[PDB]
Length: 179
Ligand SMILES: Nc1nc2c(ncn2[C@@H]2O[C@H](COP(=O)(O)OP(=O)(O)O)[C@@H](O)[C@H]2O)c(=O)[nH]1
Ligand SMILES: [Mg+2]
Image (cartoon, rainbow, N blue to C red; front, side, top):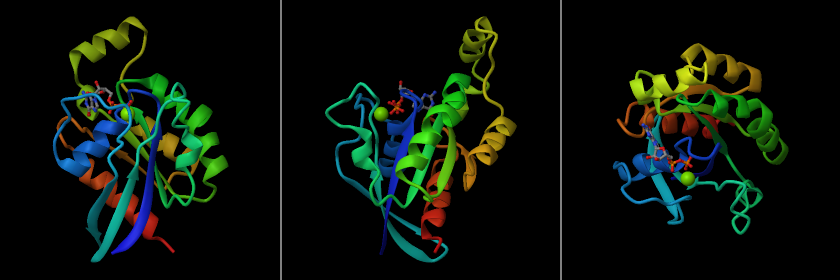
């Protein structure tokens, strides 16, 4: 297999760990783990190519003992995530994650990923955002942000329902394979 390294970044609680675990293990987790610490290397075939994809989960600022800069060397593709239930997590894409990723991983392809797509039509989510004069992120807003940051693509998924999960990793693998 062709070997590639994937790093996932984005705001705390936007669904990074659950996305990796659903992709890797095909089951939504029952216990809470801030960052996947088991070594996961996933086998995936795309366009008739066998690829081994190392999945590197990342910690928040508060985890000073496991700092994120150590994750960036030799990265082949980035998943840069926000949550569709959190317009705040989208605004951090240009203001925090893109400056960080492009600093440490110049010229590495980025897939922008909108997580928790199942919450777009969730009424608890709608009600809570409405009290803040907010609403769920629209797909067009994600695509616009993908243009702004020079992402290779924009994808939406739900780790909870599995919708779009495989496709995220397939797109990321295709990006990582580009010469
Ligand atoms: N509704 C919904 N909740 C999700 C989804 N993915 C994760 N969550 C929840 O969001 C919270 C944060 O998820 P986690 O993967 O730990 O986020 P991380 O901090 O980015 O690693 C947890 O309560 C998860 O159960 C999803 O696709 N849909
Ligand atoms: Mg996590």
